[PDB]
Amino acid sequence: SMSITRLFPALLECFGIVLCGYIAGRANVITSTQAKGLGNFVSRFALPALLFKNMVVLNFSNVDWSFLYSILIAKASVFFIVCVLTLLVASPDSRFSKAGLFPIFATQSNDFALGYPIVEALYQTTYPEYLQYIYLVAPISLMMLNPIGFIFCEIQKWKDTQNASQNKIKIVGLGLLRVLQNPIVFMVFIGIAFNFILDRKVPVYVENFLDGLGNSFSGSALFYLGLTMVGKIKRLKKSAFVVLILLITAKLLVLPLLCREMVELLDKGDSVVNHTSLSNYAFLYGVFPVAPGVAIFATQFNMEVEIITSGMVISTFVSAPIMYVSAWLLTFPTMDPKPLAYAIQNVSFDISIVSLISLIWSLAILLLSKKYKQLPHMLTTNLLIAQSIVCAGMMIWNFVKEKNFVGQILVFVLLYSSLYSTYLWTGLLAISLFLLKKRERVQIPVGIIIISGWGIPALLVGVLLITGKHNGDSIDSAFFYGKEQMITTAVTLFCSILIAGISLMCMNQTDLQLTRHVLLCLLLIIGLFANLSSCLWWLFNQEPGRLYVELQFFCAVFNFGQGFISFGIFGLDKHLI
Amino acid sequence: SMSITRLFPALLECFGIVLCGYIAGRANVITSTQAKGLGNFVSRFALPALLFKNMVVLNFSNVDWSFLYSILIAKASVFFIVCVLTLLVASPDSRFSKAGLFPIFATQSNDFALGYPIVEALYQTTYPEYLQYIYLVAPISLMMLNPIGFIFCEIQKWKDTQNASQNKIKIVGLGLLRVLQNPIVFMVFIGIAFNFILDRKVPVYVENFLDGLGNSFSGSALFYLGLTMVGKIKRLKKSAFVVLILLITAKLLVLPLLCREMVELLDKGDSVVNHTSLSNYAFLYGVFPVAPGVAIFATQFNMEVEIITSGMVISTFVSAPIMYVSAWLLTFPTMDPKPLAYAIQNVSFDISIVSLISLIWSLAILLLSKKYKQLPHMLTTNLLIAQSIVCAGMMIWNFVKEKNFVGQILVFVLLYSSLYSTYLWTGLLAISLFLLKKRERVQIPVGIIIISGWGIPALLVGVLLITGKHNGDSIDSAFFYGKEQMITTAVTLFCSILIAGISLMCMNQTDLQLTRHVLLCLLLIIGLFANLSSCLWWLFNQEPGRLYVELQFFCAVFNFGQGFISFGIFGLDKHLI
Ligand SMILES: CCCCCCCC/C=C/CCCCCCCC(=O)O[C@@H](COC(=O)CCCCCCCCCCCCCCC)COP(=O)([O-])OCC[N+](C)(C)C
Ligand SMILES: CCCCCCCC/C=C/CCCCCCCC(=O)O[C@@H](COC(=O)CCCCCCCCCCCCCCC)COP(=O)([O-])OCC[N+](C)(C)C
Ligand SMILES: CCCCCCCC/C=C\CCCCCCCC(=O)O[C@@H](COC(=O)CCCCCCCCCCCCCCC)COP(=O)([O-])OCC[N+](C)(C)C
Ligand SMILES: CCCCCCCC/C=C\CCCCCCCC(=O)O[C@@H](COC(=O)CCCCCCCCCCCCCCC)COP(=O)([O-])OCC[N+](C)(C)C
Ligand SMILES: CC(C)CCC[C@@H](C)[C@H]1CC[C@H]2[C@@H]3CC=C4C[C@@H](O)CC[C@]4(C)[C@H]3CC[C@]12C
Ligand SMILES: CC(C)CCC[C@@H](C)[C@H]1CC[C@H]2[C@@H]3CC=C4C[C@@H](O)CC[C@]4(C)[C@H]3CC[C@]12C
Ligand SMILES: *[C@@H]1O[C@H](CO)[C@@H](O)[C@H](O)[C@H]1NC(C)=O
Ligand SMILES: *[C@@H]1O[C@H](CO)[C@@H](O)[C@H](O)[C@H]1NC(C)=O
């Protein structure tokens, strides 16, 4: 069905080159002026050669058109809903610029740079005909959705001049011609024409030239995307933070769900396995992040540039685990229950690799910058040390799951001590935030706080060791002692979430970077709430089923990739070192 | 043996991407500052990933070392002789900078970016094990030849500083550490180490990342070479012109012959066909042009930068036909004569294609710039028109070679009229140069000159039609009427070469760009001398053989690719348009 084993190397390639571009950008290896030359090559030479080659050899007799217009209908619905509420809820003075750029932001995926290698990895050896749908949807979506936005931004541009009847021909033709000036649209126009002229075959004198210019698009576009991302996050207020969450949620969540529903409604027919594979491919298409062209478009308009640029550089990072989690969730009903446990173990192993490397970087940054002596930052350093042992414990646990009983007990004790320590360390950080906000001075001892965070989980692990039962022959780490282990994880998560939730709500009612400290506490609380519910689900219901498998998978991701979320918040920060 | 059919698409890719980079550079699309970012990307991310990937998977038990050290011995001999005569003949004030940079220029090929696709095209489907010798020879050559040059350039820097006992450890260690700072050398060290560490297998999590970063090296590297080549030729005097000719001749002529001779002397054994293929691969390896890294090194040393940069951009342009001609000359002994004629026709067709496109460009540049009204350019526009008719006539003759007798006769008449006009237009241009040099005013009429140049070849064609015989069932155009056609081509070439040779020698003894006009006349005179000798060879000797095939091939190349030489001399010029 789907080669879900070879998706994680593709997500390593597509974001490791982006990380290389970002590292080269901050390092001062390639400045902003020099990054413009790399973008000029990619956007004028490599991308047109790639589009022209792949549409000359494209077979229009093979393409299932039902799938094609279902994906566009899904994208049209997302565009339709985002434009309507942007018109209702925004201020009249800038209602048109947002209504023309926000639905473009929520619909235009990064298909050619990020989407094509991921689809290529999952679908080359099983359904090789699904790769041509990338080159079909992205330019068709450009011609049929982008002109509608450009009229709205040009209407906002008419407002500043504030004269004449705006001469309605003059405005809609600029948006249509702005679309046609994109290199993607007319190279697709030339490729469709040359598909019938050359009879679906590239000339032999030109075949190698187009391959050499087209195969250089992938690595250089991801590198330039990483160079684009340097320092463009800026600071945003609550009203821009909230609209950014709403837009990125729209692009990465409700567009893929709309794609699945419209494909099952409109692409009717075919065999069941083909229908299921088409549905799975439809979910994967909507998860792709926003193309960097939208930030370019807001730049040329000089309208809502900060929000759209921040939205693009955030969505590319945020979509990296969403592709992985969503695709592995789709292959779960197709799998037998017994090798499903190996699938859960494989996902946690691949996540713990990325989480451990990012945690080493963030721990090194916090240690070398000597910021750990600061009052908010001491508790963060213990937390990051604890999260690193979790990821390293999964590396051990994957290879010793069927090993000797004594080694398994030691690995389980170490792994669950670090997991339980992570749970209460979120609450300790929240209590420290409440202490820095109100009740000036008379701060609690950091050593006593560290002793509680290091001792209470150890006491819980000892109680689970004393009162727990032996055996536990399972491939998953969460099932080794039985109901005693799940009761201990439920009590630790419920006490920590209630303590941190009270301290976080009390902080709002009441360099010392309290602006970002809170969000690292905030994103973990949603994780502890999902951790508590699965422990509650197992005790009250002993039957796995319709969502226990999905909830157990989500328990694995927020346990062994919490360092990734912490690194994204903390590690990418400017220091002296 | 060798897939010589698919070499010309590889040379089309490898020089079309270079031409695209040069066009983007001159167009002002990518300036010098912006080209630095693309070069930073290529040289710091794409090339190290390519070297590391291709050396991790390399099989050291498969490599024939005899070929490897034969190629290195040939390069060492070229380095030794160039250093020796650079030490003997140069001025004492700057003998060391030239002696350290000229043999690097004459030994260091551009074998990654340009060499790897050509070797891949000629040797993927027949002898796929020959591709690893590219990644083997260039870094070993770097480590074993570059430090000697860096000692010489650091001796020249000590000379300029002029103090102390020059502390020979300090200098030979600067040269060695300058060698070790190259990205190629230590990435090859890491790849050799990881070949034994990883047991000759790339890890699966890193395989796709290394493929994505390595597959983007070729096109972006050729593009950056083209951006590097913009406007760096400059002007040079007689001595620098002569030393440039000597250096590029050394790199592109005597290094491949030394490679062939040392491979047949040192790589003893194997089968006969394997020995012949190894010899052909050694010649193809030696034809590769100079890397732009030599110009980078001359820039960082700040000595002989103009000479080395001009040498690199000239060797890169000049090597494009030398690879094609040499490789098609090597496969001729392995071919029967009857499809050797088809091989000659295919070479002439591919050359006439490139010559026609470059001639269309140069004719458009000369027409739009309105420089054809100038005194020397009127004969040049007619000459370029005539050479375009030659190339289009070869295109027709290639496609109508087995067609009706009347169309073949018309095509032959048109082709040989245009060829004889090209022959005599060199002499008319030389006579015009002599008229513009001495005997001021009283210039000859341009209309009478055009009438002479268009009628005498038409009269010769009419005489060959009247006195020639019918039939001529041959695939080559040069054999249609028999000895009458070869006598007419010999008389036209001998009269034109003698008239142009007398006028060119009289010009030296005696914007109006007389500096470049002469060289276009000069490069054609060597062609007319080679054209005359093959006509003389056929009349005095009626037996084809040991060099008649090679001389007929060279007649084919200089008949249907003279437009390429003319475009390389004239078309790449700054105008107003
Ligand atoms: C996961 C394993 C499997 C996949 C394989 C992954 C491959 C591994 C590869 C990884 C490399 C990643 C590629 C991008 C390069 C990093 C740089 C970057 O983005 O910088 C940008 C920052 O970006 C942010 O600020 C990100 C915002 C999100 C942070 C929280 C993530 C929560 C995810 C939860 C999602 C739901 C979870 C799932 C639920 C279903 C811009 O940088 P800047 O402008 O300099 O700003 C920083 C400086 N400043 C802050 C001081 C201003
Ligand atoms: C041939 C068909 C088969 C192969 C396929 C080929 C693929 C086809 C692809 C072709 C594209 C070529 C790729 C290079 C890019 C072009 C631009 C370029 O280099 O310009 C450079 C100039 O370069 C020169 O000055 C050239 C010097 C040589 C000219 C004479 C050639 C004679 C060859 C005879 C050899 C022996 C013949 C054979 C005997 C065995 C840089 O320009 P610039 O720096 O601005 O300087 C110029 C301006 N200025 C003068 C005003 C200062
Ligand atoms: C296998 C799965 C892999 C998953 C990877 C993805 C997940 C991991 C994700 C992320 C981890 C790394 C995040 C780095 C991003 C921040 C960089 C930064 O801010 O720039 C820094 C500079 O740059 C350096 O100092 C670079 C350090 C060397 C490269 C280390 C990255 C290793 C990536 C992993 C390789 C592991 C090995 C993998 C193979 C076993 C700081 O500089 P500054 O002070 O801001 O400014 C510079 C000063 N100046 C401007 C004055 C000059
Ligand atoms: C199949 C075999 C193919 C073999 C091809 C390889 C051999 C052919 C070789 C050479 C062909 C031509 C080379 C031109 C190089 C000079 C450019 C130059 O000087 O810059 C020009 C600008 O740029 C332009 O105007 C570019 C012209 C369009 C691109 C070239 C089209 C033809 C290329 C091939 C199509 C092949 C089609 C194949 C498919 C059928 C002039 O600019 P300027 O004013 O002088 O100076 C700049 C100053 N300014 C910035 C202020 C303006
Ligand atoms: C649930 C999935 C499918 C949809 C994606 C929504 C979530 C995960 C995304 C969308 C909006 C995102 C936030 C938007 C902006 C910022 C500010 C940045 O400085 C830190 C990360 C942070 C706080 C992001 C974290 C992840 C986030 C909350
Ligand atoms: C014979 C082969 C194998 C070796 C290569 C030697 C010949 C073809 C090369 C080497 C030196 C070259 C010349 C060096 C410098 C220039 C100046 C430039 O503005 C026009 C071209 C011109 C005049 C080159 C023409 C081609 C050239 C004569
Ligand atoms: C999908 O296509 C047809 C649908 O009838 C059928 O061969 C099968 O279900 C699938 N085939 C392939 C090759 O995927
Ligand atoms: C070259 O290698 C051996 C030489 O003994 C022989 O198989 C043949 O000549 C050649 N084989 C291949 C595969 O090239």
Image (cartoon, coloured by chain):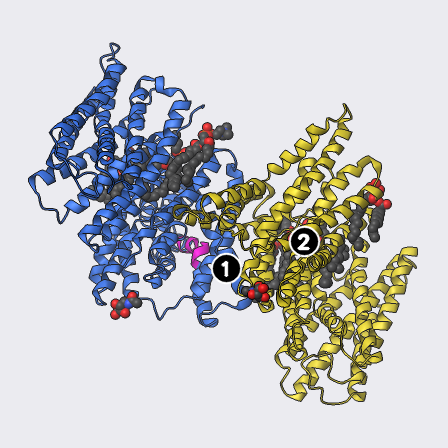
Chain colours: A blue, B yellow
Residue A168 among magenta residues:
no
Q: Quadrant of the N terminus of chain A?
A: bottom left
Q: Is residue B380 left or right of residue A381?
A: right
Report x, y in % for residue B149. 71, 39
Disc 1 versus disc 2: distance between alpha carbons? Answer: 34 Å
Q: Quadrant of the C terminus of chain A?
A: top left
- Quadrant of the image occupied by residue A360: top left
**Residue found 92% across the figure and 56% down from its top:** B509
Tell me which chain the residue with mark 2 is part of: B
Kindly tell me whether residue B200 is visible in this rendering: yes
Report x, y in % for residue A495. 15, 26
Residue highlighted by disc 2:
B70
Callout 2: helix, strand or loop? helix
Above/below status of B210 relative to B1: above
- Quadrant of the image occupied by residue B2: bottom right
Assess mark 1: CB under 8 A from ligand 4? Answer: no
Tell me which chain the residue with mark 1 is part of: A
Residue highlighted by disc 1:
A211
Residue A183 among magenta residues:
yes
Report x, y in % for residue A270. 23, 67
Front residue of this view, candidates A381 and A344: A344
Front residue of this view, candidates B210 and A410: A410
- CB under 8 Å between callouts 1 and 2? no
Amino acid under label 2? Ser
Report x, y in % for residue A539. 9, 38
Amino acid under label 1? Asp
Q: Is residue B565 left or right of residue A255?
A: right
> Which stretch appears magenta?
A175-185
